[PDB]
Amino acid sequence: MDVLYSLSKTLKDARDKIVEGTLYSNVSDLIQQFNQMIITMNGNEFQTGGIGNLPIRNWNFDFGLLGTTLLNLDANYVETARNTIDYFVDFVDNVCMDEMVRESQRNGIAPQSDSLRKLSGIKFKRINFDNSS
Amino acid sequence: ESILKKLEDIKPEQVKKQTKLFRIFEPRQLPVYRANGEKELRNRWYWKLKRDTLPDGDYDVREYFLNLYDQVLTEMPDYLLLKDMAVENKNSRDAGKVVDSETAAICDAIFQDEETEGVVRRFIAEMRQRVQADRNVVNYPSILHPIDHAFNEYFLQHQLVEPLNNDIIFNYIPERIRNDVNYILNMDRNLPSTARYIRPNLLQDRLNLHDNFESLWDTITTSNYILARSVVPDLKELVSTEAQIQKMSQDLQLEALTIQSETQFLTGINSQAANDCFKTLIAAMLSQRTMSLDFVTTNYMSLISGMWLLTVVPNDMFIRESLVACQLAIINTIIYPAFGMQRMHYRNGDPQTPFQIAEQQIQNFQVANWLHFVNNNQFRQVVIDGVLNQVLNDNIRNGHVVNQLMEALMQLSRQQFPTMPVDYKRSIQRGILLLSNRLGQLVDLTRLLAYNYETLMACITMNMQHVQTLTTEKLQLTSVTSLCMLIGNATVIPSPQTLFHYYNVNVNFHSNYNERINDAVAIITAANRLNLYQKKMKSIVEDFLKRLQIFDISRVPDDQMYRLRDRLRLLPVEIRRLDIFNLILMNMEQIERASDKIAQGVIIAYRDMQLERDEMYGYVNIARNLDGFQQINLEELMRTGDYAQITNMLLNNQPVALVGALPFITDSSVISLVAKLDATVFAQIVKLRKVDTLKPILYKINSDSNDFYLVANYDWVPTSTTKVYKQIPQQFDFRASMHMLTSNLTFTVYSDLLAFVSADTVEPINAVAFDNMRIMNEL
Amino acid sequence: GVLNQVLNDNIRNGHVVNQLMEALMQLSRQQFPTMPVDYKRSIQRGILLLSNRLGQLVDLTRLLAYNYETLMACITMNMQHVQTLTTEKLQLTSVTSLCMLIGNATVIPSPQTLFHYYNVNVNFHSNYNERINDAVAIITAANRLNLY
Amino acid sequence: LVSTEAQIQKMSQDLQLEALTIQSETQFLTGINSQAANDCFKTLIAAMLS
C-alpha cells in the first residue's frame, strides 16, 4: 500500500511539476524520486488480474531515466516524461482497480491482488516516499 | 614501460595435454598362503599404490590428499586424443592397440605369466581398439583400477575444447566492431569440422576489487591506463605549431613593451602536448582512472580550454580538489567579471562546486545553461554485450555540446565587464576568440574523442567501474589547449589490428584473473573441507596475486591477503575442480587404506584373539574394523597433549583402540608372537607422553616364518592380544579392470582466433560516427 | 581470596571489536559536510586502514585478554585500583604499530614464565607479610617493655 | 608481525599525506615498527596487571 501510494504520489508530482519552462531546481528532487522509481520497477513483470470483466493486463518496465541536463524544462523533455508517466499511471490505476475488486475474510487488510503482493517485497521499498495523505 | 611489458606479456592460458593415464594403483604379484599358512605355488595379483608415500598422522594424511588434489588438478587435461597414448598389444589377435603403455606392460606381464589362466589370455587376445571414423570416435582397451578409471573417465568426458568454425571466429570479434561500418573484415580459410578451440573464462569480477581493495584497484586501473595509452591512436596532420603560434600572435596583438596576460596564452603549445592530452583523456576514460588538473591561474587560455574540457569530459573523472580549483578560476576570471558579479567567495569543503553556485547565481541563460550541463554531465552506466561500460552523453558523442559552450562563450564576449579595466575584457575576448576561431575543429575533436573512446571501449572485457582511484593521472590544461589549437581535419581511428591487440590483451588478463581465482578458491575450499586447521592460507593468496602478474606482493600486507581469502572463500568452486575434489573425497579413505606404510590404528585388547586368515598374509593380527572397542583419537591427543585418559587406560589394562595413521613393524616370527611382543610397545606412551613414536607390531605368520613348524605341528591357530586396524589389498581382476576409453579420433586445436581475421579500415575521410555522419567535417 | 580486575566478556572473546568496526565503517561513509575533500579522503582512508584489519584486531584483542588473564592468575596480592601519582606514558603511535602490525601468530606465556611470575609474586607477598610481622612485633615489644 | 615496510607503504599510499598540506608530513608515520608494537603490547598488559 505504501509502495503503491508512493508510486501514485510520484506520478502525481511528475504530472503537476514537469511542465514546460520550469526550473530544473523546481523538479530536481522529484526527478531523483522518479528515476529511483524507474530503476526499481525496471525488469519487473506484473499481471493485473482477470476477476470479473477486468481485462488481464501484462506490464513490463524497460524505461530510460529522466534527464538532468536542462536548466529549464523544454517541450521535448515534457513529452518524454509524459510518455513514461502515462504508462506508469495506466499501471497504477490497473493495480488499484485489481485490488479494489478483491476481498478476503481471513486477512482483509493484507493485499489481495498479485501485483500489490509483489510490490510488498523489500526490493520495492526504495520507491517509498512522502506519505502525507 | 615495465607495466606495459608485464600486462602484454601475459599469455592466454597454457593448454594441458594428457600423455598417459593418471594412475594411483598398479597390479603387483604377491605370494598367497593356504588357510593354514602354507605357501601356495601360485601367486596372486593385487592392487597396490604406485607411489606408496603416505605419511604418519591423520592431519598429515589430509595434507597428503590436499597435495594429491593439487597433483590431479595439475594433470587434468584441457583435451585428450587417445591415439597419442595408444601402443601395440603384442598378444592382440588382431595386432590392435591399447592405452596407455602402462596398460600394455600389465597385459604383457599377465599374458606371459605361467600362472595366468587361459581365459585371461583369451581376454587379452581380444583387447583391441575400434575406430568409428564417421563419428570421429575411437575406443581403446585399458587396464585401470576403479579409482584410476573414474579419474580418467572424468578427464575424457569433461574436455574444454569446443567445435571451431568460421562463424565462431567472426563472432569472437566484439559486436560493436563488427557493427561498425568503418571496418571491413575478411577471412581466407574455411576451418574444418575437426577444428577446436578453448573458450576464455570471461566471468565478471567475483572479488569486486573495485570495492574496498583500493591499493589493488589502483594497480589494476594503472595497468589498464598504460594499456589504453598504448592503444590510443596518434594524431595525424596536426596544424603546424609554428604557423598556429604565428596566427595566435596575430589574433592576440602581442605588444613588446607591455606586460600582457595574453602572452601566457601561448605557453605549452606543441604537438607532443596535444597528442599527450588526447591519449590521457581517452585512456583515463577507458580505464576509469581519476584525472587531476594541472594549470596556472594566470593562463586564461588554460581556463577557456578547461571550459571545453569540463564540457566534454564528465566531471567525476577528475579529483574533486582540482576540478573545484579549475571551476573557481573559471568563475572568478571569466564569468563573474564578465557580468560584473562580486568575486565568488568559495569555501574549501563546500558541498556544491563553484559551477553549481554560479549556475544558481547567473542570470544569463546561455551561460547558466552551459553551467547546468557541466554540473550534470555524467557517464551513463550501461551493460553492453555483458560488460559494464561508461557511455558518454549523446550530445557529446555528436559534438553538439560544443555549440552550447560556444553560445555561452559568445554571451561572455558580449558583456561589458563593468568593474574591470577595458584591457581585462580585451584579454578575455582574445582568449575566447582563440577558442571560437576553431569551433568546427572543436566539434570535430569532440566527435573524434568520443568515437575513439567508444570504439576502444568495445574491446574491454572486464566491467568498467567508476570509482575514484587512490592516485590520479595528471592532465595539464596547456595540453588541452594544444589539442584544441592544433587538431586538424585528419580523422584518426584505431587500427583493426590495434583493436584486436587491445581486445586480446584484455581477454588474456581477464581469463588469467578468472583461472587464478578458480585455483585459489578450489585450494581454499579443499583445505577447509579437509579440516586443515593448522594451515595458514596466506601462501595461497600470495601465489594468486603473484600469478596475476601485475601486483607487487611485497607491498601487499597480510591483512589484505586475508580479506582476499575471505572474499574467495565465499565463491563456488569451478565445476571441473569441484568434481575432481569430490572424487578425491569419495576415494581418499580407500586410497589411504591401500598404503602399506601406515595402519589406520591399533586395538589393545587384553584377551587372546585368533589371528585372521588372509591369503596374502597367512595369519595376521589385523582388525577389519573397530567394533566393540572404545576409540582414542590420536590426532586429538597430539593436538591437546593431554595424556590422562590414555595413561589411565594403559595402566588399568582397559581395552581400547588408538585410532590414527600409524607406522607399523611387520614381524614374521612365531616366537615373537608367542613372546607377546605386540603387547610391549605401548608402555612408552605412559613413560614419555608421546604417541608419534608408537609403532604397533603386525604379525605375518606363514610358511616363510622361520619357526612355522610350531603352527604346523600343534594344530595351533595363532592368537594375539593386539590387532592392527588395517585393510587387506583388493585382488587384481584383469577382466573387471578392463575399460573401453572413448575419445575423438583426431582434431586440431587453435589458440589465436583473430589470426584468421584480416581487417582494414575505410578511408578516414569517410569514417562515420554513431550518427552516420563523418566523424570530422572541416575543410 | 585475591581481588582481581577482570574484563567484560566481549573484550575477552574480541566480539566488541566488530562493534568498533561497525562504528568506524559508518565514519568512513560519512560526508564530513564542511571538510576539505582531500583531508576527508585521508581521514576516511585511515579509518578504513583500521577497519579492514577487523580479523587481526579481534585476534589481537583476544590475545591481549588471554595473556592478561593467564598472568593475572599468578597474582597473589589484591589488585587494588587507584589513580597513581605518576603514570606510564603510552604513545598512541605504539598503539598504531600494534594495531597495524599484529599477525596471526599466537603467543601465550610459557609455563615456566608463569611459574616464575607466580613465585616472584609469592615471594614478595610473603616477605611483605613477614616484615610486617617483624615490625609489629618489635613495636609492640618496645611499647610493652616501656621503651619510651 | 606484518612486514613494517609493506604496512608502511600501504599506509602511505592510502593516507596520501604528501598530497595534503600537513605541516608535519614526516612525523605522521614515525614510530610505526615492530619494537613499538611489542612495547605497546607489554605496556598494556603490564599496566593492567599492576
Image (cartoon, grey):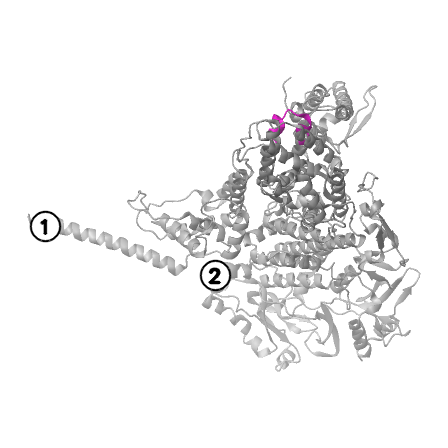
Q: Bounds of the magenta span?
A: B356-370
Q: Position of residue B546 (x, y in %)?
A: 63, 59
- The residue indicated by pointer 2 is B643
The answer to whether residue B718 is left or right of residue C81 is right
Query: Disc 1 and disc 2: Cα gap in Å?
Result: 58 Å
Residue occupying image coordinates x 78% and y 72%: B102
- The residue indicated by pointer 1 is C142
Circle 1 crowding by C-alpha within 10 Å: few under 14, some 14–19, many from 20: few
Chain identity of mark 2: B
Q: Please tell me which residue lies in front, B333 or B597.
A: B333
B444 over B272 or under it: above or below: above
Circle 2 crowding by C-alpha within 10 Å: few under 14, some 14–19, many from 20: some
SS type, badge 1? helix
Furthest-top residue in view?
A133
Three-letter code, disc 2: Tyr
Q: Position of residue B275 (x, y in %)?
A: 70, 49
Looking at the rendering, in which quadrant would you find the N terminus of chain B?
A: bottom right
SS type, badge 2? loop
- Residue B13 lies in what quarter of the image? bottom right
